[PDB]
Image (cartoon, rainbow, N blue to C red):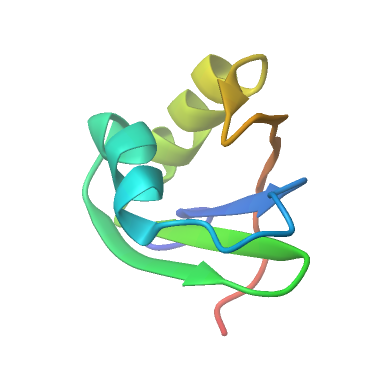
Length: 78
């Protein structure tokens, strides 16, 4: 009920990305606990693994922030 519930996001813009824009994109897949943006990647913590699978399935070919995002199930709990 916890494992595999975080979405890794790469290929974000170099310019600052709004957490509200990320929320708008990804909240339809499930409840979002955390949105964390780092220099070269970010993550979205959901509360269940199905949300992550669905986000990957549905958003991997979309242009979001002007990018085809790299989407994966994260192994991080940090």
